[PDB]
Image (cartoon, rainbow, N blue to C red):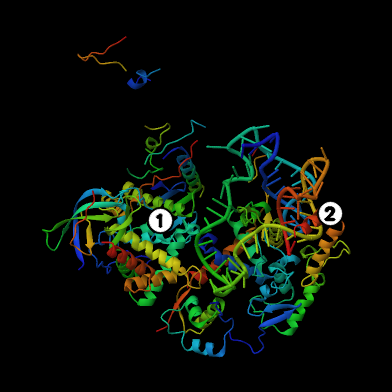
Amino acid sequence: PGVTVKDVNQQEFVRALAAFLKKSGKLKVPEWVDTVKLAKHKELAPYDENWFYTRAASTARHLYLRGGAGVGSMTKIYGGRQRNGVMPSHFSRGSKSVARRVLQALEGLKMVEKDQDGGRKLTPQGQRDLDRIAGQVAAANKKH
Amino acid sequence: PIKLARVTKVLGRTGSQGQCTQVRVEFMDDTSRSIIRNVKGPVREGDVLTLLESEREARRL
Amino acid sequence: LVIPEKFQHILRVLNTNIDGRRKIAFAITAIKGVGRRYAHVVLRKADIDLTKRAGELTEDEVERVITIMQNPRQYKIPDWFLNRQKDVKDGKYSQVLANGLDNKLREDLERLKKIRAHRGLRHFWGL
Amino acid sequence: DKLNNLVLFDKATYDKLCKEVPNYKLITPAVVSERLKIRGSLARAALQELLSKGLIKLVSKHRAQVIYTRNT
Amino acid sequence: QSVQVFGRKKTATAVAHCKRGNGLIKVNGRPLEMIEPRTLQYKLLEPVLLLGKERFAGVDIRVRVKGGGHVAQIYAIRQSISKALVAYYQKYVDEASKKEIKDILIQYDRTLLVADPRRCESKKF
Amino acid sequence: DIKLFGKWSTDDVQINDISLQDYIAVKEKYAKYLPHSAGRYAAKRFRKAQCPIVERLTNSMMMHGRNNGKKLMTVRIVKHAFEIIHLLTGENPLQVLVNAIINSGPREDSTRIGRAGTVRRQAVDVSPLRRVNQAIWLLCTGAREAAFRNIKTIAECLADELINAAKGSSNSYAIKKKDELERVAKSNR
Amino acid sequence: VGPRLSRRILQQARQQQEELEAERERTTRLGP
Amino acid sequence: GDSIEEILADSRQRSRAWLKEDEPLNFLDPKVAQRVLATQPGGFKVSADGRLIIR
RNA sequence: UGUCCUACGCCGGCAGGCGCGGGUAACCCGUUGAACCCCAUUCGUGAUGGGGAUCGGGGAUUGCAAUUAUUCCCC
C-alpha cells in the first residue's frame, strides 16, 4: 500500500529531495562548488548555486533505480553533446571529480554504501528515507 | 458567377510534361450540360470542382 | 519592478563604457579581457545576485567587483583560471583586462619580432 | 528601424499596464512586449507579478509558451 | 488464470502479462501517467478512454519494454496492452465481448492489434 | 465522446464547401485524440485525403531543415495555437481551420507551356485535393515567414494566420498568394 | 516476426515470467 | 525424411527463432509452441502429341 | 570491434596520472544509462548570451623528434 519512488513524478522528487538534503545540512560541500563546470562540454557555470544538492539528489535517485554504479557510470549518465567548433558534435562524459565527490558525500551521510560487486549502492537508511520523502511528495501532489 | 460541377470520366494526362489532366465535367444544377476541362492536380471520378467562368471548353492535342 | 531613481545607463569601468541595460554577468563580459565565465565567477565571489540588472548597482558593489577583478588570487579565484599564468618576463599569475591586454600583446609581438623567430617575422609579413 | 524596448518600468508605462493589461482577451509575453515596448524578460516578470495578485488567469504553461486570459 | 502477449514497433518490443486484479496498470514498474513523454500521453490511454475504466476494473497488467525510441516504445506499450486485453477476453471471458472489443479497436486504429511492418532499409554495394 | 486534446469537440464542425467535403476529414470516424498517428498514408494515391486535417497541418509544420522530424514540437505548436485561437475568437478552432483552408485554396491556377522560345501561361482548374494541399502549404508558409525574427512565437503567428484566413482578410499571406494566383489565372484565360 | 526481434521478445518474456515467479551463506559444513 | 518433396529433391544459426502473427499470441498458452518455428518459413521440350522428349 | 576494449578505487577543476580486476568474447566493457527529443530556468530582435574563425598565455598526452602550432584541456 505504501507509495514507491517509481510511482512519483521524478522532477518534483529531485526538487524535494534536494530541498531535504539542503535542510539536513550534513552534506560535505567542496570548496570549489562555485568555480567548476560540470563537464568539458559545458560552456557556463550552472545558475542554480545549490547545484551540489540537486546533483546529489539525482545521484541518490539513480542509485535507487539502478544500483552498482560507479564513478564512470555517473560520468556516462550526465554526459552530453559537445559542440566541437565548426566540427561535428560528439558525445562527451561528465567530469569524474564531481561524480566522485557527490558519491563520497552521500556515503558520508550514511545514505550510500559500497558493495562487493562494484561501486556504490543504497543503504536501508537510504531506501526508507527515499520512500518517506516520496510519500511526502505523493501526499503533496496526488492528494491535492 | 461561381459554378460547381462533378467529374464524370477522366480522359487522360495532357500537357507537355503531363502536368494537366483533360477530363469530362458535368454540372449538378442542370445535369444536361457536358464540357471538357483541363485541371492541375490528382483527379478521379466523383470529384466535384469549382469553375470560375463556365463557358469555354479546354483544348489540347 | 519599476526604474529606481539612481539607474545609471552607461558606466565607466576601466576606461570602458558599460551598457547598464544589460545583465551584470554580461555587462562585465562587455569589458575586454573578461568573458562570460570569468564574469560569472567574479560576480559570484562578490556575493551578488545574478538575476539583478547592472545599471542600478550602487557604487560599493561596483568597487568591490573591481577590487576582485584586478585582484583575483586574493579572493580564492583559482590559479588555472587566469589569462596570463606564467608571464615570460616576471612569472606571476595575473589577469590583465583593459589596456594591459592590448599592451602585453604588443610587446609579445615585439619580442617575437626582435628575436627574428618564424612566428613574429611571419605575422609582421602578414601586414 | 532598431527596436528600443525598455528594460525597467517607467511610471507612465507601469500605470497604463496596471490599468490596461487585465483586459486584452490575449495575455502573452510577446504581445505585451510588442504593444508596450518592453523587453521580453521584464514583460514575463510583470506577467507572473500580475498573476501573483490574482488579476490574471493562467490557462496553460510551457517552457516555450505560457498563455493567460482575463478573470471575467 | 493469466496470459502473456507482445507488441512491437520498429525495434521497440513490449511484453505484457495480464492477470486478475483491481485495475493497476504498470509499465516498467511505473504508471501510464508517468511514462516519459506527456505529449503522446493520450496515445497511452487510448484503450482506457475507448473501452472505459469499468472494463479495466478487474484486471492487472504488467509490461516490460525494451528497445526502440520514446515514440516506438509508446506504440509497443499500447499494442501490448490491447493485445493482452483481447487475449484475456478470448481465453477466459465470453467470445462475443471479445468480438465487440476487437471490432472497436479495429475501426478506431487498425495498428492496435497488428504490428506495423516498417523498418529501416539496408544499404547495398 | 472522442475529443481532440481531451477538450475539442468535432460534432459541431461543418464544411461550407461541397468541393472539399470528401477531402477534409474531420468527423466522427476521423475524430482522434492526437494529431500523431504514424500511419502509412502515402503508400497509395488519394490515401492522404482520409488523414485528419490537423495531422496534415502538423506534418506540414515540419519544414526547413532543422525542424524535420520534430513532430512532438509541432503538436505542441498546434495545441498552443488552438488554445490561442479559442481564447481570441471564443469559437472552436477546428471550424476556424476548416474555414481558413476553404478560403485559402486556389480555385484557378496557371500552367507554364511552351514550344520554342514562346513560354506562356494557360489557365486550368485546381482539383479539390490540390486545393487542400496548397491551402495547408500556404498557411504553414505564412506562419513561418510571419514570425522568423521577432518576439512573436510560432504558435501566435500560426493562430493569427488561421484566424485571418478564416475571416478572408487581406492581411494573411495565404489569402494574398491565392489572390495573386487567381488574378494571374484570370489574366491568362 | 524474424530472428532478432523474436529473440529479444522471447528473452523479455522469459525474464518477465521469472520475475513474476520470484515474487544466505553456502553450506560449508555438510552435516546438520 | 519420407516426405515426397524431400525425396524428389535435386540432390548461432540454430538459435534463430520465428514467431507468427489471427489471435494475439499467448506465451502462457500450452499450445504456443506451434506458433514458434525453428526454421525459415516459406526442363524438356514437349512434342506435338504431348509426350516428353528424353535424351 | 577488442590483447588493446575497459569495469572499479584514489588524486586533480579539466585534459589526464597511480593501482588492482574482467575479456581470444552473445560470459567483460554492456540491462552498450548516445544525441536529437521531453520538462523546467535565463536570454528578447540587438552582427546580441546567435556565430565561431584567427590570435596571446599556461597545463597534459603519443612518440627517437611536435619548430611551420600532431592532438586534447583552461582562460
Q: Is residue E108 visible?
A: no
Q: Nearer the viewer, mark 1 or mark 2?
A: 2
Q: Which mark is residue E21?
A: 1
Q: Residue furthest front?
A: F117
Q: Are marks 1 and 2 on the same chain?
A: no
In the rendered image, the vertical position of residue F98 relative to residue A68, given as above or below: below
Question: Disc 2: which chain?
Answer: C
Residue C71 vs residue H17: left or right?
A: right
Quadrant where the image shows the C terminus of chain F: bottom left
Q: Position of residue D13 (x, y in %)?
A: 53, 87
Residue type indicated by callout 2: Ala
Residue type indicated by callout 1: Gly
Tell me the distance, in whole angstroms, between the alpha carbons under discs 1 and 2. Answer: 84 Å
Question: Circle 2 is placed at which residue position?
Answer: C117
Q: How many marks?
A: 2
Front residue (pair F187, I24): F187
Q: Position of residue C24 (x, y in %)?
A: 67, 76
Mark 2, secondary structure of its residue: loop
Q: Residue at horizontal 49%, vertical 52%?
A: E69
Front residue (pair I49, H20): I49
Mark 1 crowdedness (10 Å alpha carbons): few <14, some 14-19, many ≥20: few
Query: In which quadrant of the rendered view does residue H34 lie?
Result: top left
In the rendered image, the vertical position of residue F36 relative to residue H23, given as above or below: below
Front residue (pair G29, A38): A38
In the rendered image, the vertical position of residue H39 relative to residue F171, given as above or below: above
Q: Residue furthest right?
A: C90
Q: Position of residue A34 (x, y in %)?
A: 72, 68
Query: In which quadrant of the rendered view does residue F110 lie?
Result: bottom left
Residue H50 vs residue A75: left or right?
A: left
Q: Position of residue I53 (x, y in %)?
A: 67, 57
